[PDB]
Length: 231
Ligand SMILES: CC[C@@H](C)n1ccnc1C(=O)O
Ligand SMILES: [Zn+2]
Ligand SMILES: [Zn+2]
Image 1 (tube, rainbow, N blue to C red):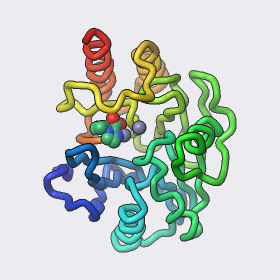
Image 2: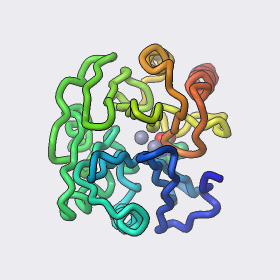
Image 3: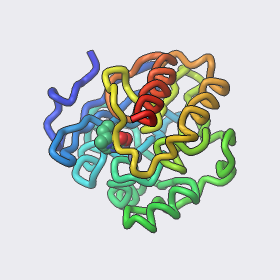
């Protein structure tokens, strides 16, 4: 069973093996009066690991690296943040000090600097236009357009048919919008449709927060965004 926000003390990180060489990482964080789970991805890259997103904070990201060393025992050599928010770049300094090469699009680095969040060192070129995709080792990076944020990327693992949607994709149990302060509500369904059109073969869909599912998380998210738009 997938670890839920109830089973994880703020400060611990769980790993969940989705497929051969693919895991999600799950942390918890307190925010605005509540506790939320948060997902990222780990993808084996030969004898190294590619990390997708921090574990939401320096303390959680330290624990994430410890859990990876304990349960997998391969070095994290590169990390990609999928947008500029704290649940995605909070902990980047921890990764860089541990020798991880940290990456984000110039869009994400720009917005993180404006916001005062941690800034990944390296830039991912070739993702500034909606529908752009670039290979990054064992994953493909995709910019679907503005959704949860203007810079949000999704990540596809071709070998395992795993689509990591990040915060642009909601889990089924979430029936109201989350933090939409930086969102483009008007474009979000269109951006989700680009994901569906580009990855129709996806078998495992991982939202930014909560339980994984299939491609039906995409239509669920569009439904929730439209309902919010209409409120
Ligand atoms: C999922 C709950 C909301 C508040 N949230 C917390 C952190 N990130 C988000 C998001 O919307 O992506
Ligand atoms: Zn966000
Ligand atoms: Zn988020």
